[PDB]
Image (cartoon, rainbow, N blue to C red):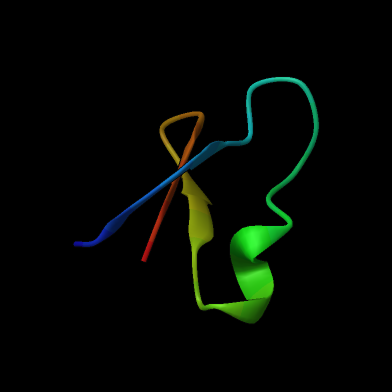
Length: 29
């Protein structure tokens, strides 16, 4: 799993374009 730094705590991941999915409130690939 790749931590994208960004999280989906407040709002969903913007890093979804990179393939980062909202996983445990954090954006992980």
